[PDB]
């Protein structure tokens, strides 16, 4: 028998859509994610012989990747960047040979990336869809807005609508019902499996504490899924495969041979040279072309040496065999103690691979190829395991998450949900398409204000600032519509403005909020 | 055989000393910690028949508790508060009976607290010292300033000086060498055990990942200490006893019968009534007298019901038996799989008990009494276990922590450490007591700038604001002294100002920075 390795990547970005501007600072997050992570995954799926991988692509992120104005902006961003790449291959010619060499790597690579983007007429969802069809990739949905559902457990209508909207949104893009779901922050509370069952969801992921703190602990601990009484399968995180293994402070990515994130030519190159690749404001930002390796544990960032991609590859080769040997060792020990095949569930934030850690997808590819050769280990997707397992225990998971004033926001959320439900029931049978448009945008506004991102975020250079500004912006938009509706004075131009800027789920139906609960 | 339960409380606050003001906002953190957590622990140690508990009291916190100007300010704060308590027992008389009843609880309780403080001539360290002498309490030290040591691993001089200064500071207050140490954030890197051995430290605590990710995993996992090759014992966190069990979102403290933190009369009572118990600025803040229970998962905080302390006690009784039954169950399972007694290591932030969770120390007391009666379980301190264990495996822990630009700060830290070392060696043999005073305050300034608190803090209502302001303030003070020294123009009045405001380790000796490493 072989141990089963289930690698899970969580691919999420908040819905950030600013069509009122031509370059916006927080739309670059999306572009870096596409360049650094999503397309290099595609490249890696194409190049590798075989893999098995499960991932989320959250509805906000599907809605952005499919938006053909973002695709146009990305294409223009990629050209600006290939232009810079060229400027850089000449300017580097008389500088360090490593630095010169990298600039040419960067030119070829960026060309390759934009070319893959073009292969798919700029919808890279089509690429992910195509790997799902092979069965090598398994893509799960997420709640509609990546709201943290345990915060809203007293408002089952918004919770279940969060789920349904995600499910339908996935169907729309993927042309297939989702089988599994990733809850934002693994936020799970008791009873939530019922709504998942109502939504025809087959499996979700929980934190380890969901099994440890259950009334009776699952017999095989976190190394086999359980089935809830409702028939929904839960997969618990292997805490031995935690966040720390990917830490720069203590894990593989902190290796001195790896590319340094916080050195970039947008901070180093002379201002007149670099002007129209930074912010139009004139402020220095990251470009994506970076020449230094981490070098050492020094606090003196000026002492950083130039990146050598061959040593970097030597590091991934070592790390990938370290991790392999650790999983084989863990598998063998578990088989011997358990008597059935362990399934080792290891979820990571997607951007950790290729974005925070430049060499991450290279690592992923080498680890897959190694697991493929291993006689102790098999890659599985999560739907393969639910389709294959015969013994599975039945258990109920404990409230939990994978977890890490300011209450003007909360009482406003409370009133918005309460009002949204009232009005959805009140206008359930309306055929007025203006009232419907209004109610539909109210729900979008409400969902947009629920993003966990704006609350206790995974915002890189975010800072509780653009975030609480985001939340209040959507609260205010919702209240404006509420006021126009409640008083006969629907303002059609404002409504169209809102429909345009906050365009997330075009197919939504406010009537989701009028359904029964409990 | 019985399972061994090792409860660990981490008691830390940053050094915040503002003698230039008469009330300062961030000196109230200390007062709430004393009132809500440190004295009620003392009360609980006195009242319980028997307990075993290990805790840190970090050097910044010992230095504040012993400062007899803070003790005077606390005494005056406690009287202001007992005065408010009295105003409240009358004003409540015709309001809800729960609310009236609580106000009288609050009067008696605050009187009791200030009275314990007086029992000890206002040094409550004397109380903690007295329980260490019984052997029921074990108090470990921490690095001098709760700096995160893996950030500084390339500067072994500052690392080892962080350790030594803590060790000596503990000796000064406790009149005993410390046997164990708690590293800030369990930040551990390979080699750090050597410096601990050099400092005569017998045991430290690491994160679970320190064992899981070791070259060979410890045979008994996290349920027995290991000994490093250097002879230093490491105790790994039981991840089944994690932070989540004390979560308000998913754990016991979130029970609707428990006292609500974010309702306080300083926000509710009328302004003219409440004026001289809030900020002198006139801004509303917490008073410490709070009348509501959590009530429900509602986002509508206005719907909160009044606190009933008897139901709250019924909740602690249930929770304490839940936790007991979970630890007995875990013990029995482990004994049967291991063949020796497990030691279950469960560390918590101290303020989680009594401060975030009002009923926390009550819970602690009931859990101890229950464990005391249990036939499956024994309370142990960490020094009891190192003194008792005969089989212990030898292993080397992996880099790890219990873990969760902006680089002007870093290059300044780099230069300050580098300069501090130079000058400590250069003036090693000086007998000039002015140069010595200067060098001694430079080191304080440097250490104060290293506080992890100011970096990725455990700041409640802190916000990366008072924090980076703190860091830069100490950087600037250090550079001022550096400049005066390097140029002959030591400014004695400024130096005395610094000695007064930043008075942390009076006994320090800058020569710690001139020692060998490696």
Image (cartoon, coloured by chain):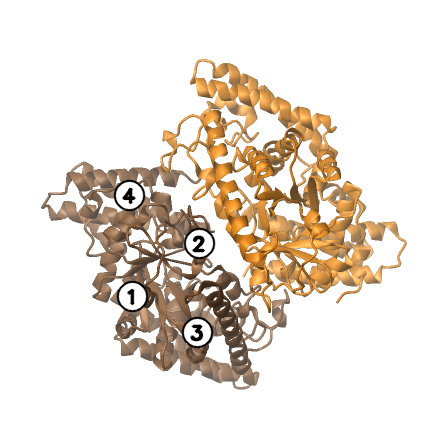
Chain colours: A brown, B orange
Q: Distance between the residues labelled 1 and 2?
A: 26 Å
> What label sits on residue A156 in the rendered view?
4
Judging depth in this view, the residue of B86 and A139 nearest the camera is A139
Q: Which residue is rendered at x = 57% and y = 76% of the image?
A: A257
Q: Which residue is rendered at x = 36% and y = 60% of the image?
A: A13
Q: Which residue lies furthest to the left in this view?
A: A431
Judging depth in this view, the residue of B451 and A241 nearest the camera is A241
Q: Are marks 3 and 1 on the same chain?
A: yes
Label 2 resides on the chain identified as: A
> Residue B42, located in which quarter of the rendered image?
top right
Badge 2 element: loop
Residue B368: x percent and y percent?
Answer: 59, 37
Label 1 resides on the chain identified as: A
> What label sits on residue A402 in the rendered view?
2
Q: Distance between the residues labelled 3 and 2?
A: 26 Å
Using residue B21 as the reference point, say whether residue A176 is left or right of it: left
Q: Do labels 2 and 4 share a chain?
A: yes
Q: In this view, does A276 lie above or below A431?
A: below
Q: In this view, does B447 lie above or below B285?
A: below
Q: In this view, does A465 lie above or below A296?
A: above
């Amino acid at each position: 028998m072989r141990g089963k390795i289930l690698i899970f990547l969580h691919a999420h970005l908040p819905y950030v859509h600013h069509p009122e501007y031509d370059h916006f600072l927080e739309e670059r997050w999306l572009f870096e994610a596409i360049t650094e992570t999503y397309i290099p995954l595609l490249m890696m799926f194409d190049e590798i012989e075989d893999f098995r991988l499960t991932m989320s692509i959250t509805p906000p992120l599907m809605e952005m990747l499919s938006s053909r104005d973002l695709q146009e902006k990305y294409e223009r961003h990629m050209e600006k960047l290939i232009e810079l790449a060229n400027k850089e291959v000449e300017r580097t010619k008389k500088e360090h040979p490593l630095k010169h060499k990298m600039a040419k790597f960067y030119r070829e690579h960026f060309e390759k990336i934009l070319n893959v983007f073009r292969s798919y007429d700029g919808n890279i969802l089509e690429g992910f869809k195509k790997y799902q069809e092979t069965g090598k990739l398994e893509i799960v949905t997420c709640n509609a807005t990546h709201a943290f559902l345990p915060l809203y457990q007293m408002y089952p209508e918004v919770v279940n609508a969060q789920i349904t909207v995600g499910v339908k949104n996935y169907e729309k893009h993927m042309k297939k019902h989702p089988r599994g779901i990733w809850l934002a922050e693994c936020g799970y509370y008791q009873g939530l499996d019922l709504y998942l069952a109502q939504n025809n969801v087959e499996y979700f992921f929980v934190d380890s504490h969901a099994f440890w703190f259950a009334d009776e602990q699952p017999r095989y601990g976190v190394y086999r899924p359980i089935m809830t009484p409702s028939g929904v399968f839960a997969f618990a995180r292997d805490p031995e495969s935690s966040e720390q293994v990917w830490s720069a402070a203590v894990g593989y990515p902190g290796d001195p041979r790896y590319r340094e994130f916080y050195r970039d030519i947008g901070f180093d190159r002379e201002m007149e040279y670099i002007k129209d690749y930074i912010d139009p404001s004139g402020v220095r930002i990251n470009t994506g072309i970076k020449y230094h390796r981490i070098t050492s544990k020094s606090l003196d960032a000026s002492q950083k040496e130039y990146y050598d991609i061959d040593l970097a590859m030597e590091a991934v080769e070592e790390h990938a065999r370290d991790f392999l040997h650790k999983k084989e060792s863990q598998a063998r020990r578990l088989m011997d103690i358990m008597g059935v095949e362990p399934v080792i569930v290891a979820p990571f934030d997607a951007e950790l691979f290729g974005h925070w850690w430049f060499e991450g997808v290279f690592f992923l590819k080498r680890f897959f190829e190694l697991v493929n050769e291993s006689k102790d280990l098999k890659l599985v997707t999560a739907s393969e395991v639910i389709d294959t397992l015969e013994e599975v225990q039945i258990a109920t998971p404990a409230d939990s998450s994978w977890g890490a004033t300011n209450d003007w926001i909360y009482r406003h959320l409370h009133e918005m949900i309460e009002r949204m439900i009232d009005l959805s029931k009140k206008y359930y049978n309306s055929s007025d398409p203006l009232v419907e448009r209004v109610l539909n945008q109210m729900l979008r506004e409400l969902f947009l204000a629920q993003s966990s991102d704006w609350a206790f975020i995974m915002t890189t250079r975010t800072s509780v600032q653009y975030a609480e500004n985001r939340t209040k912006l959507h609260i205010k938009r919702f209240l404006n519509l509420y006021d126009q509706l409640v008083s006969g004075r629907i303002d059609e131009e404002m409504l169209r403005y809102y429909e345009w800027t906050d365009a997330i789920f075009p197919e939504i139906n406010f009537r989701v909020m009028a359904r029964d609960v409990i």
